[PDB]
Length: 41
Length: 41
Length: 118
Length: 116
Image 1 (cartoon, each protein chain N blue to C red):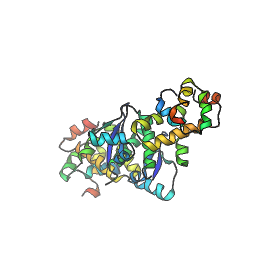
Image 2 (cartoon, chains in turn yellow, green, blue, cyan; image 1 turned 90 degrees about the horizontal axis):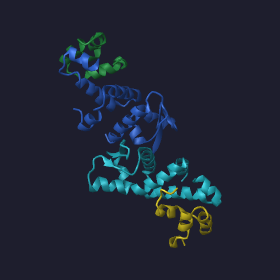
Image 3 (cartoon, one colour; image 1 turned 30 degrees about the vertical axis):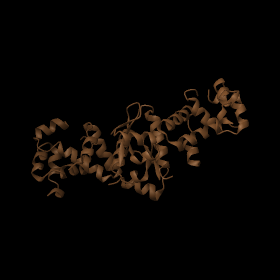
Image 4 (cartoon, each protein chain N blue to C red; image 1 turned 60 degrees about the vertical axis):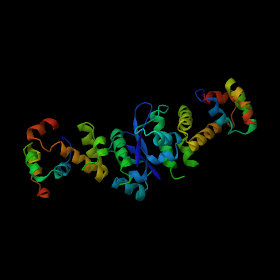
């Protein structure tokens, strides 16, 4: 799952409850990078 | 045509104007028999 | 509403019942028997896809130009379409396909007919 | 009425023109260009068929979706891309939620593995 541009990845992540982003942040550097995105909080 | 059921051949022949059936009858054994079908005349 | 049609070789096609219903027999199975995967043991995927295409174009219903171009297929596919139309009881399909073969007979000698159809 | 959609791999799909009501991308191509055969260079036949199947089911607008999306992970990824490309908002939304539900309740390890 890297062929999805960041926008779609944030689309998926935005479905999660905030604390759930802690899980996505430890998965991958892209995920770590995208999980802190200004728009998810 | 090795497979169409005779009922389907009649369906094809039914689309021909009558004089045309003379052609069909001169093609082969089966065609001659079906060309003579009650349902066409 | 839609239903799944399953070809003899297992491909599943999700089809609008309004499209599938031109097959008189599938119409009764979907509306009356209420069959989940409608099995069609005598139609393969390649031909079923073409039958569905025709049904999709004709869902709102001389050979119409669209049908003439749709039927510009090889002889074998045309005969398979006749069979499938017969099997599924799709009258309009059966008509146009039989008409198409009839046109390959018109204005030809028995000798020319033998040749083209073998 | 039907129109032809052409997948990236050349397969033609005769589809009910009503799909336009769901794909803004196809709608633009249909209305704004003509394109009898509507070319969709970013979607292959396998995924296009599934997209058409989802639109057909949803033309009259969930548990059916849960069943429909109970498929291979790479396929799920392709569906997200195709919903985005074709701009079919409802398909995009349920596929991203489906993916989020595979993340939810799991630890980074599983997540890495399942989507590995």
